[PDB]
Length: 283
Length: 288
Ligand SMILES: O=P(O)(O)O[C@H]1[C@H](OP(=O)(O)O)[C@@H](OP(=O)(O)O)[C@H](OP(=O)(O)O)[C@@H](OP(=O)(O)O)[C@H]1OP(=O)(O)O
Ligand SMILES: O=P(O)(O)O[C@H]1[C@H](OP(=O)(O)O)[C@@H](OP(=O)(O)O)[C@H](OP(=O)(O)O)[C@@H](OP(=O)(O)O)[C@H]1OP(=O)(O)O
Image 1 (cartoon, rainbow over the protein chains, first blue to last red):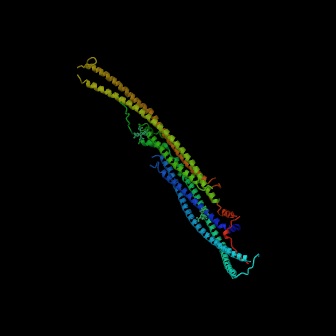
Image 2 (cartoon, rainbow over the protein chains, first blue to last red):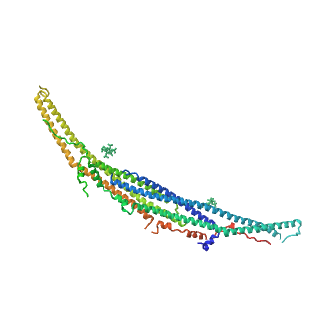
Image 3 (cartoon, rainbow over the protein chains, first blue to last red):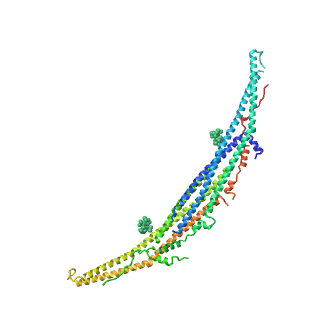
């Protein structure tokens, strides 16, 4: 946390590009997680839908124990589905949230990067202009230096004198623009290095940490949602109140009693021919 | 208490008319219960199969790869994988159950067919005997009618030899005696067959049908319980999958993340170093 090393590296040039790249990576993690969650909640939603639909067929009709018990365990199926529905709802909510996040953060990063590029460019090209002017100045001065040696004469005439004077004026002007452009460039540069740069990298750091922490929280949420789902279905099938368990329903059937019911019911008939033949004569 | 089927209404019900042999229908109903259940669990393991497939396929389809997060997400997706595995096991169990119930249904159907046909056949035999008796009766009564109509005639007719009323009388008397013996015989035959059917065979048939019904239904109930334990196993196993009996749980992964530390690593890692040629400052130095 703000070590001499970290503070040392944060002061260099590559920093501003580096943590931009980092932030980009973070954005990518976000988008990735979005996609995953979407696919997940999609097919899970599918699962729920069929789960809920399918059990409502079969034995849905309203007189026997077994059929009833089956009806009930299919009911359990339904309950499970409702739980999972709650879960997918949670997932959807999450997705929307992290989407909004990603949007905001991408936009923000774009802005910061633009600003950075602009400022840095301004400084750099200012320096460029300065060093150009420098080159000019040094060139003219180099010629004037070339003036002053294995040479002949020359007292010269009005022409050479005029050339000298003119060149001196030229060098004077070039010198002034040189100096002022240098001071300008250095001013801008130092203003950038001392104030703007650390502010930008500060902002980018803050952003990265923000989005990272948010997403990690989101991951933890996904986790607790999942284990919530699993646990609750787990306690849905086996509520710890045994009378509500699935095995509880499946346990109580008694077919013999239902058969006795069938027959004893049939008691409360049918001739079917097979009436015997009687023998009697008539003399 | 057992011997509920040994009660008065029950015994008189089964010992009653063909209404007993109701049991065929009931066995049919149980068979339809079987088939319906099959249909259901078929649909079930179908869409569960779909779910599992998509689970595994989708889980494996993303990261596959350096910060903490990437790792952690990779892990929780791994957990998704484990879940897919256990649910696959569950599906396998379901399919097995399907096969078993199917075989059961087959057996029971074949048996029902056989028994029913047998019953029908024996009943038919009885009915045929009765019919024969009725025929003999008709013949006898007819010939008696002929006699009683004949003795209203006062004269001789020529046929075999020739004449007469008296001889015709005696002849017809002989005929009717024969027809009468036939009658009595076939009556006794009929009634004997009937009694033997009612007292011996029919009970055995009823017994068999009842036994079959209880067999299939009990079997299907234990099957239901099997399905229940299968589901319990599934959910319990996914449960213990995502939270093992450890430091390698899901909450453990999701909980433990670097963020600040590995960012410090990321920065301190940059330490030769790229310095910008565009931002080299410029100095002003004059010239003599
Ligand atoms: O077209 P490319 O050669 O593949 O380069 C692009 C481009 O970067 P440059 O402008 O420096 O060439 C994008 O910049 P923009 O068009 O959006 O202004 C930049 O996007 P970011 O500035 O938002 O980072 C993107 O990077 P990324 O793929 O992380 O989005 C990067 O692609 P490369 O990193 O593969 O070079
Ligand atoms: O009890 P099952 O062994 O399954 O046989 C029944 C029975 O036929 P049988 O009396 O010849 O044994 C039905 O007859 P009823 O009880 O209605 O008098 C008949 O119904 P239909 O006479 O109306 O055709 C039905 O046939 P289906 O399933 O087409 O309705 C047929 O079942 P099977 O064709 O499977 O033998």
